[PDB]
Image: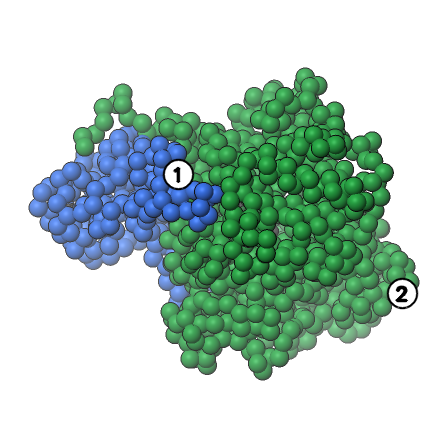
Chain colours: A blue, B green
Amino acid sequence: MRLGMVIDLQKCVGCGGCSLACKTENNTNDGIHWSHHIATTEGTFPDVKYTYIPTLCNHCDDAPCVKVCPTGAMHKDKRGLTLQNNDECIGCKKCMNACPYGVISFNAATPHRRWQDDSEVVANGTVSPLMLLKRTGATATPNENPERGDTYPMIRPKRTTEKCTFCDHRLDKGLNPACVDACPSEARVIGDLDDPQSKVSQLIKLHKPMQLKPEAGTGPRVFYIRSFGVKTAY
Amino acid sequence: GAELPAPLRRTGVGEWLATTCQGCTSWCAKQIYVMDGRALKVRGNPNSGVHGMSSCPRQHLSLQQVYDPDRLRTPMMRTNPKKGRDQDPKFVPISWDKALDMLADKIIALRVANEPHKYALLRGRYSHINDLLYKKMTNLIGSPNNISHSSVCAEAHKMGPYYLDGNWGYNQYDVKNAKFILSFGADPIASNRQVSFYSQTWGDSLDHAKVVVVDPRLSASAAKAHKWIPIEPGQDSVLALAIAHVALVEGVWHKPFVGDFIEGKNLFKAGKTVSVESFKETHTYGLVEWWNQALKDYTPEWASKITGIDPKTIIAIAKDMGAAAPAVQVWTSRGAVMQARGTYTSISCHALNGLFGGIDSKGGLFPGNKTPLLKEYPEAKAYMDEIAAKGVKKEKIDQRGRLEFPALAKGKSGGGVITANAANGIRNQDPYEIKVMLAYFNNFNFSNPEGQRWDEALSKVDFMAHITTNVSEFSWFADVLLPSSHHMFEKWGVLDSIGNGVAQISIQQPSIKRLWDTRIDESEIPYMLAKKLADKGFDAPWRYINEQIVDPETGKPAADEAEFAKLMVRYLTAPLWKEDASKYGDKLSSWDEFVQKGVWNSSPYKLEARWGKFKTETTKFEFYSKTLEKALQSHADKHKVSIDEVMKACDYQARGHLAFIPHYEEPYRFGDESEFPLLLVDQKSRLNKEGRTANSPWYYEFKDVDPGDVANEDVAKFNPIDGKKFGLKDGDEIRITSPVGMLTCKAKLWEGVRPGTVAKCFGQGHWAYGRYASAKFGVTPRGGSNNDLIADRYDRLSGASAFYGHIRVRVEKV
Ligand SMILES: Nc1nc2c(c(=O)[nH]1)N[C@H]1C(S)=C(S)[C@@H](COP(=O)(O)OP(=O)(O)OC[C@H]3O[C@@H](n4cnc5c(=O)[nH]c(N)nc54)[C@H](O)[C@@H]3O)O[C@H]1N2
Ligand SMILES: Nc1nc2c(c(=O)[nH]1)N[C@H]1C(S)=C(S)[C@@H](COP(=O)(O)OP(=O)(O)OC[C@H]3O[C@@H](n4cnc5c(=O)[nH]c(N)nc54)[C@H](O)[C@@H]3O)O[C@H]1N2
Ligand code: SF4
Ligand code: SF4
Ligand code: SF4
Ligand code: SF4
Ligand code: SF4
Ligand SMILES: [Mo]
């Protein structure tokens, strides 16, 4: 089994809804986005092309982040996913240097520290992050998703790395990744690339698949098909 | 920690509750995922026939609005009797009873003094239960001044559809079946009125539709289009008119809709008039008169000289649209039409929807489907006393209907709101002073052009109360703050949406326990205020509510605030769930089923339904708008002048016949071009939930999803040509100055900007709202406020404020 994702760039409108869904799903600290993007502008006016490429962990066939991890915290599971036992992460950052794609973040900052602020913009009138935290019963942020704790810390400790888990906790329940459900055009599809009849397997035979940095030799399993833009008419 | 054992796992077991998003007038049906009493996720309501589960990205930002750490938790009163941008209000907390006591005393004082018309109700956003607070309460008090925000929105965008085919309203666009899409400034995968559905369909549609986007900037939509036309701001109608000209010369109008020459031969030759009697129109009126009076001379070469567009491109577009007809749809955005002469851009662009037959056709555009939703509570005439009956006849504070403010909504002189001009009437106490103001869900100091005029106006109002979640810029000037329960998570309401060939009606309901000591703007607060007014000797609002707004099943009035909030929605939606709505769409068995599904869908639109029966003077699609002539004649007769004198008084160039046909108005411009060499291209952020996500950190974290923009910054985008000309580099702190004001932000060089323009998102520049949206709350803004640059100007035929085309600016570093 080799789970992976196919992203249809013609369907994609570059809105970031996938990345925002990832924020709500996985309780990433402010500034940490497991799902993100690579956007480029090319050409000189008036012949200008803008392209948006959504990015995530490619859950590689030959993951360097796994090979360099001294504790074994970063590992492959039986679905082909690259996951992390956060409890065994010593924050050495070797995975970040080994990953060619820059999709791993390091919790140098105390996650959700801004919610400990108890100042009020209008005293005894407006509320505060800390008060809102107390009112809702949340531990770190009122937006924290408890589902995440099924398989991974809902709130990660400082001095650990983290990245896209392919919403493994949702897959365990037979559900879809949050970013897949969040896409208005159904541009994102996941499946078993070892199953020739899966939608993903058929998509990359029906369309020419493209990968990010295949020359790095990791065998990424996020594939891009088609084109964000179209050739200019007239 | 270890993975949890299956009996203790939590993924997927929470509850989904239906509501409606209002980040834009798409008004998408949603479900909220709730666990441990907290809202954790938003998704599109799968039962929605318009958009299904599809959503734009802003749905997730909703979660940082309800859980905004700068929301008000209590009513407040200011203790600084002075008001002003420089005056700290020194708000202190008070009870609801005390806050409404204060407001109630001021209202009753107006009535005792026979000046009820000096009360004003200001409405920003709203739901379809607004009639009580907006209209009925206001008129029962005795005021004509229920002032919506419609004219700072898109009323100019309704002029074409109304005066050509009788629709004072918006259209849905049949993208799934389109063969040609021509967008004058619309960016439907980022803004406009069904971002979820048009984002769902846009990329797929490129395989069967040729798409041209006309916009001074390379928008997301233009980046996914076959042609980007980087029009000079305010010149859109030149292209629309030349397309129509070529269509006639080439003989490729849609004959099943328009008609044809009696003898078959195409007699339209460039520059030469045609006999009206030689053509037989079918469902249109005025084609030949339009040609003879103007269109015969709107050649591709004439258009190329003004716009720089290749005439071969104009010709090729016209032919492509002819071959695609009737699967042709022309979009207009605020950008094209919210200009001082923009009524005729709406008309000129929308005329193409008739000429190529797209109106009410497959692949074209058409109005929202009919639904049985009620929009008003019962008439209140029997509850109007003599004080109220006299007050409601006074001239409105926004001066609608004066010679220079026709505001011809639905064909009526003084028929339309003039939101931005209410500040001027208040400012000048013309027609009279406003002494008591209630406002909700609005922030006109920030959202209206030259909003400092609202700073001034509000500082001159004896008593104002603001119904709001946050202390926004408008709130700064309030005497009393009345904190609103959040519309999307703590409120009963009802909304609608159109697209995908259907109209839907969706519920708003509380999905969490109310966080703070707030009340629902449109139900609980007017209810509580009516009780307070009745306690003080004015019980007409209370009697109206208790006798006329009763449960559709039990016939009983509400027993308390919470019951009334739901009753307001039950009453207007009863035709959907109490009665059989099968004739219009879904059959619902009960109120509970309506709430559980969360949405009612109409049947699919019947194509060509309006052909031959438009609500125009002729009942035809009017290229020569007898409908508009009649409205202008009414206004002219009212003021004892000719129509031409109305045109002159309203700073339009049209005279004679040109007042009634698609024609070219040179765009109005303000300021010396030598001193102010750049044209502002105002745009929305695709992460703006109107003016309400600037206090959401996730907004800034992903701000570069706006093509060309920069995460965690407010940037103005310049073409590198102008960057070199003005010595600008990426990241430079800059000041942008217009004749009426200035702002500071950062510079970004981007080739997707037409040279000679500067493209900058509206949405930042808050100095209040919250700690993330401002640098120093109440003092110093984050980013720059676009509307401080935009001179207070109007499309006087519609009443609309102008946000585009006339704004000249200069830029400098630091
Ligand atoms: N993301 C987001 N979407 C929204 C909203 C929001 O707040 N945020 N608000 C909703 C609301 S209330 C409204 S009324 C609708 C409005 O939706 P629209 O009427 O479709 O237009 P705007 O979204 O206001 O965007 C204006 C566009 O016009 C362009 N333009 C500016 N000047 C000119 C010109 O002179 N000629 C031409 N051809 N184009 C010009 C700007 O670049 C910009 O792309 O959007 C709704 N959709
Ligand atoms: N330069 C520029 N100006 C524009 C636009 C643009 O594109 N460019 N778009 C214009 C358009 S299309 C629109 S329709 C107008 C809208 O203009 P407005 O109607 O003034 O809307 P907002 O700016 O969003 O202000 C709404 C305010 O309601 C309060 N509030 C926030 N959330 C809630 C809630 O849940 N309940 C209640 N009771 N109150 C709440 C806050 O005070 C908030 O500032 O702005 C317009 N102005
Ligand atoms: S949600 Fe879908 S359309 Fe939007 S950026 Fe992500 S993949 Fe693209
Ligand atoms: S994308 Fe990077 S983090 Fe993800 S599996 Fe590959 S090497 Fe590891
Ligand atoms: S930072 Fe953690 S996951 Fe990465 S290599 Fe070091 S121990 Fe392994
Ligand atoms: S698969 Fe899940 S963890 Fe990965 S980017 Fe999508 S939402 Fe985030
Ligand atoms: S912001 Fe507008 S388009 Fe986006 S989900 Fe909300 S209502 Fe729909
Ligand atoms: Mo609007």
Question: Along the horizontal axis of the image, is B738 left or right of B652?
Answer: left
Picture layout, residue B699 above or below residue B270: above
Farthest-out residue, left: A70
Which residue matches tag 1?
A: A132
Q: Amino acid at mark 2?
A: Val
Q: Where is residue B109, by image quadrant?
A: top right
Q: Where is residue B296, by image quadrant?
A: bottom right
Q: Nearer the viewer, residue B625 or B206?
A: B625
Q: Position of residue A142 (x, y in %)?
A: 37, 38
Q: Amino acid at mark 1?
A: Leu
Q: Nearer the viewer, residue B519 or B693?
A: B519
Label 2 marks a residue whose chain is B
Number of numbered tags placed on the structure image: 2
Q: Position of residue B748 (x, y in %)?
A: 42, 69
Q: Position of residue B489 (x, y in %)?
A: 49, 35
Secondary structure under tag 2 reads: loop
- Of circles 2 and 1, the one toward us is 1
Which residue matches tag 2?
A: B641
Q: Quadrant of the N terminus of chain B?
A: top left
Q: Nearer the viewer, residue B436 or B351?
A: B436
Question: Along the horizontal axis of the image, is A145 left or right of B23?
Answer: left
Mark 2 is surrounded, within 10 Å at the Cα level, by few (under 14), some (14 to 19) or many (20 or more) other residues, namely few
- The residue located at (60%, 48%) in the rendering is B479
Q: Quadrant of the C terminus of chain B?
A: bottom left
Label 1 marks a residue whose chain is A
Answer whether residue B87 is visible to the viewer in this image.
Answer: yes
